[PDB]
Amino acid sequence: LSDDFFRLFLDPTQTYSCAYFERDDMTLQEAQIAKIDLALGKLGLQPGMTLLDVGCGWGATMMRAVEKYDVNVVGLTLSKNQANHVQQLVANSENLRSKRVLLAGWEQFDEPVDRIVSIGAFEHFGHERYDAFFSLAHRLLPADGVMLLHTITGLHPKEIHERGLPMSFTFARFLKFIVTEIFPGGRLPSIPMVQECASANGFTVTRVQSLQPHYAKTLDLWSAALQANKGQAIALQSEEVYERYMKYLTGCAEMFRIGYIDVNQFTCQK
């Protein structure tokens, strides 16, 4: 799936994650900005500090940090195209603030940093190395370092409650199946798991903000946008991919509408 395909429905910043409609009247793009600000506004960034963006994407977050918090910034991505893109954007920076993009994984970064931010990308599920991750977050942040993790989470067996659906172990397991195999179709971390993995590597989860409502609308806006470009979509990929996404976007939006799927920002203050 070409990056061109996703550009058919994502906003100009190409943010493939939950948007934050701080205002109901916000556009997908404004919501993505607010989401980024929501994240950043939680790190207590001070001019001169160095921010690490784990999974910088097309760079919207980095640039926003430099702009509103006047800080140096290091971004990591496993996407040649995203690195290329941000690297070009960063070229000839007169700004008295360092801006660096790296085509490496977080497990290969080893630099003193003041604050860490990690906003995941939708279909990128693989939260099975969270323990080692905090160890690294700890091993890089200042004594009062702070990190924000924006991730999709799933319901912990003993975490559900008060939704109006069966409370059995059989129903939970079925939903767990649906969630891991179809919508979204990957293994998701539970809120307890993150709070626990963090509380065991030198961190303390100060806040857990849910953006569940917002994702329903984000996905709603992505599907509408995609449908409006059905022609181009079928032309870049095929009618099979187009349909797959329309129903995968639709299905995932519903999983949030029942709560077995959630998206949280975890302020991890150490």
Image (tube, grey):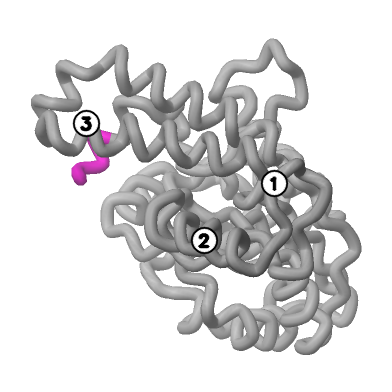
Q: Regarding mark 3 in the picture, which secondary structure is present there? A: helix
Q: Regarding mark 2 in the picture, which secondary structure is present there? A: helix
Q: Regarding mark 1 in the picture, which secondary structure is present there? A: loop
- Left or right: residue 101 versus residue 256 is left
- Residue 3: in magenta span: yes
Indicate the position of residue 172 as horizontal and vertical percent values.
62, 62
* Residue beneath disc 1: 165
Mark 2 neighbour class, 10 Å CA radius: few under 14, some 14 to 19, many 20 or more: few
Indicate the position of residue 244 as horizontal and vertical percent values.
25, 38
- Left or right: residue 244 versus residue 175 is left
* Residue beneath disc 3: 242
Q: Label 2 is placed on what type of residue?
A: Phe
Look at the image and give the residue range highlighted in magenta. Answer: 1-5
**Location of the N terminus (image quadrant):** top left
- Residue beneath the point at 65% across and 55% down: 150
- In this rendering, the answer to whether 30 lies above or below 137 is above
- In this rendering, the answer to whether 97 lies above or below 250 is below
- Residue 184: in magenta span: no
Pick the front one: 86 or 264? 264
Pick the front one: 31 or 70? 31
- Residue beneath the point at 59% across and 45% down: 61
- In this rendering, the answer to whether 150 lies above or below 239 is below
Asked whether the viewer can see residue 100, the reply is no
Pick the front one: 171 or 30? 171
